[PDB]
């Protein structure tokens, strides 16, 4: 099973041959510059922010959500009643003699309901994303993916969202809680991931079994 | 799902500088805290128990 | 559901600077604290017990 | 059950190629600004 | 029972596209204000 041909994660060539440089011009200067790549106005004191499509931005994924709720209710009611004419006087033996009124009754009712729920999620990491759209108000739509293949699998960390430029720090970084439409994904493949999927029959009994 | 509903009449001079007023300064305070789902359904007495609670002699 | 009802007559000179008056300064104080639901229904005596409480000899 | 094709959460492309910039105008200035937003 | 279609609590769209802004007037001013509320 290890002999099956596979496509690596970093496809292509993993080396680049330096290209020989242009022949200097015969102008009487030592400084000779190859065909210059112009990048447009670049500020000098403004922080390094993504401005156009293709610029990179660092997202510090730091998510900590914890919600909870709980409730209960109860009721109880107990009652006893008794009357015993242990020795009935003779003038009252027609109304109370022979246990004609001697009684003993009891009753009880109880109820106790309760319920609750809680959800939690945490995320911590760092991912560099790319601006793929600049919106009308200057906000940047950012998308990014990091793929790591360690030993016997592949993990994908994907991120997407909208970043307001004024939230980006001086180190070209923004926490993940300042991104409006945050879409964070952390998945994997291989048998390690296949071992965390419920069996089809168990996944069916989880939905269709009466209890 | 939990619903917290409130209603009442607030006198403006009771509102603090942070645009906040305690609930005891609202005249016709109607405060509701309910929920649905099976968690709420588990806190309702069974119809037969709720009938015996009202009609049983003791 | 719980209902807290109040009624009475308040003398204006008893009201403090915070527009508040203790309930012992209200002349015809009518204070009510009731509820409904099965929690309240569980605190009513059964009709037979409530009859034996009044008509039993002892 | 893990072989079922699925749609990821972050759909689309997860990369953007930087677009080449406009050719500077011939006004005698070094500062050249692309179509301003 | 978890497969039953359900209506979420926050219905509708959970995003808003920024609307492009009005074209500035030709009065010789840099400050241009959209239709004021």
Image (cartoon, coloured by chain):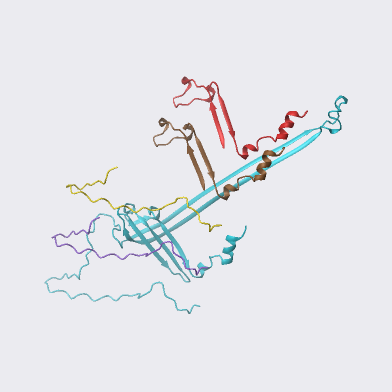
Chain colours: A cyan, B brown, C red, D purple, E yellow
Q: Is residue A199 visible?
A: no
Q: Is residue A178 above or below residue B21?
A: below
Q: Is residue D27 above or below residue B42?
A: below
Q: Is residue A79 above or below residue A116?
A: above
Relative placement, left or right, of A199 versus D7 is right
Task: Give the total number of marks visible in the rendering.
Answer: 0
- Viewer-nearest residue: A104 or D14: A104
Query: Where is residue D4 shown, x and y percent of the image?
Result: 49, 68
Image height of A175 relative to C30, above or below: below
Quarter holding the C terminus of chain C is top right
**Residue at 56% across, 33% down:** C3
Residue C35 sits in which quadrant? top right
Task: Please state which of residues A198 and B7 is positioned toward the viewer in this rendering.
Answer: B7
Q: Is residue A207 left or right of residue D17?
A: right
In-image side of E19 versus C31 (left or right): left
Q: Find residue A83 and report its horizontal and vertical position in percent.
A: 79, 32
Q: Does residue B22 appear left or right of residue B36 in this picture?
A: left
Among all residues in the image, which is located at the extreme right? A90
- Residue A201 at least partly seen: yes
Across and down, in percent, residue A87 comes to: 86, 29
Name which quarter of the figure residue A207 lies in.
bottom right
Q: Quadrant of the N terminus of chain C?
A: top right
> Which residue extends farthest left?
A28
Question: Splitting the image into 4 quarters, where does residue A138 fall?
Answer: bottom left
């Amino acid at each position: 099973c290890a002999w099956i041909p596979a496509k690596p994660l970093v496809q292509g060539a993993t080396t680049a041959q330096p290209i020989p440089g242009p022949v200097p011009v015969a102008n009487g200067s030592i400084f000779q510059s190859a065909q210059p790549i112009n990048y447009g106005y670049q500020p000098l004191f403004e922080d390094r922010r993504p401005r156009n499509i293709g610029d990179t931005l660092t997202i510090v994924l730091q998510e900590n959500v914890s919600a909870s709720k709980s409730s209960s209710a109860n009721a109880s009611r107990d009652g006893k009643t008794s009357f015993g004419f242990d020795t009935v006087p003779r003038y009252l033996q027609g109304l109370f003699g022979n246990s004609r009124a001697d009684m003993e009754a009891s009753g009880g009712n109880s109820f106790n309901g309760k319920g609750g729920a809680n959800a939690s999620n945490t995320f911590s990491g760092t991912l560099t994303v790319t601006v793929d759209q600049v919106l009308a108000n200057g906000n940047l739509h950012v998308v990014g993916e990091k793929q790591i293949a360690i030993n016997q699998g592949t993990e994908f960390i994907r991120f997407s969202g909208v970043v307001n430029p004024r939230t980006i720090s001086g180190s070209n970084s923004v926490p993940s809680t300042q991104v409006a439409d945050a879409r964070i994904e952390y998945v994997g493949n291989g048998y390690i991931n296949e071992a965390q999927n419920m069996g089809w029959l168990q996944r069916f009994f989880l939905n269709l079994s009466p209890m």
